[PDB]
Amino acid sequence: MPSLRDLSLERDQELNQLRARINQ
Amino acid sequence: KLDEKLKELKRKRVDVSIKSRKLADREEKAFHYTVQEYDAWERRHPGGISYDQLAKLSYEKT
Amino acid sequence: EEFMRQMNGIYPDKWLFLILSLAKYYISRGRLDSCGDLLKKSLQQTLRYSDFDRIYNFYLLFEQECSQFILGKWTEKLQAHMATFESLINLYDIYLNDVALRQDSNLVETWMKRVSLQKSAAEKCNVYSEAILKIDPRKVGTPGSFGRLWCSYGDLYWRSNAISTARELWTQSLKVPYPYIEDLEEIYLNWADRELDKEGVERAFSILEDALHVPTNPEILLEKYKNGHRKIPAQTVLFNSLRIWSKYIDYLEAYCPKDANSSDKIFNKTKMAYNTVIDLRLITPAMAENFALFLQNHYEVMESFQVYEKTIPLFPPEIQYELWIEYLEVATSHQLSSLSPEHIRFLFEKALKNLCSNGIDCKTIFIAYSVFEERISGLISKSIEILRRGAVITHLESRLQLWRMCISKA
């Protein structure tokens, strides 16, 4: 978990910024 | 009224010369490598001895 | 004057003193127009900044002194002289970069400064147009810099209006035979981002999918370009860009609704984008986990494990440790995993055999194995023996932790 899943959870959280532009 | 324009031009020109002269006087990081980069990095940076083995090693050194 | 030309032929090495002396002669002879155009020609012809400073300063002071002398008195001459004086004062930044446009004409950074000094965007377009023709791709030093010039040039139109003009310009950009591939990513990633805000991400996929038309025999083309020594364009190995694959995958993954399923078109497309990255061996350990977490979030857990098994063998053991931790942590505790207990034991024993065969600290896998063995069967005796195997097998602090846990549990 701490090594790669921790980074990937941040990636899936940064994609919310892309989702805002996706819907608009 | 050209005197005032000339005065302003000289004032700016002095600064231009000063600046030009000053320019004249100068005279977690490992998780992001691809598989290909790992292949490259892993290939660029990967008692007693018998007389036959010592012989081959000496030949290779020569 | 004839002797002047003769030494111009004979002594080219001290041109500065020559032009200064001949300019002094021109001023002394009353040939002010001759001095003007001579100094203009010399100033345009300078190449070193120390030489430029002396000629520029001399021109500036000559204009100042001549204008003040005429003012001491003629109107037209005075007007022209102070006009040239003010022009040379203001155009210092333009002459400054004129020097650097001859030290190295294809160094695009100077062109990105020359654009900044222009007064209006109507002129910025002209300077970009000159820069594109003057710059030759084969000699652009810093990679990924000429592409920034096309990106900025397209953005200049895009900010005002005429999106069609920006697109038609960019379609010319991708046709340029670039030497490096960072220049190509800087254009595609920018074009896709700009299209995303306007025509939706459905179009934004198309821009990147055109770049990633995977060809047959990738190894042959990668060999031809890699061993071509800048002779072969980076247009042919565009499929081998991690940054384009990453952004294409980001757009696909953000476009998949959070309740996507196997029959959804975008979810299938994301699977093909990731599987093609893995096939190309462009997958990075963070992306191999990004794929596995995407699958788990979409309840395709049993196919998440196939990602881990497809990717773990490719990386060195030091990274196989992280992916093994992820794989086993998901396998042991997740409601949708259908791995039988003998399978999860097979995974654990495989991990410990492979990693300990390479000296990697395996403390976490040993602890997880002991906890799993207590969970699944309740055989405490087997759990302790597993911990003892870890402590008995150089990472002295870990072996002291496994000895304390093994003994305390016993």
Image (spheres, coloured by chain):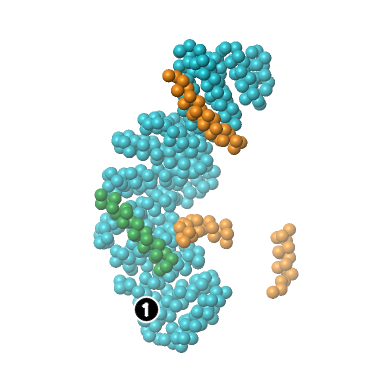
Chain colours: A green, B orange, C cyan
Residue at left offset 38%, top offset 85%: C378
Asked whether C61 or C137 is in front, the reply is: C61
Q: Is residue C42 left or right of residue C121?
A: right
Residue at left offset 43%, top offset 41%: C148
Residue C354: image location, x then y, percent: 49, 71
Residue C158: image location, x then y, percent: 33, 38
Q: Is residue C73 left or right of residue B62?
A: left
* Residue C307 sits in quarter: bottom left
Residue B56: image location, x then y, percent: 71, 64
Image label count: 1
Amino acid type, mark 1:
Pro
* Chain letter for mark 1: C
Question: Dot 1 surroundings within 10 Å: few (below 14), some, or many (20 or more)?
Answer: some
Residue at left offset 50%, top offset 66%: C318
Residue at left offset 36%, top offset 37%: C156
In the rendered view, would you say C386 is above or below C71?
Answer: below
Residue C290: image location, x then y, percent: 38, 61
SS class, disc 1 = helix
In the rendered view, would you say C260 is above or below C370?
Answer: above
Q: Is residue C91 visible?
A: no
In the rendered view, would you say B51 is above or below C100?
Answer: below
Q: Is residue C59 left or right of residue A11?
A: right
Locate the N terminus of chain C and report the quarter of the image it occupies: top right
Q: Is residue C378 visible?
A: yes
Asked whether C186 or B43 is in front, the reply is: C186
Asked whether C249 or C233 is in front, the reply is: C249
Asked whether C274 or C105 is in front, the reply is: C105
Q: Which residue is mark 1?
A: C341
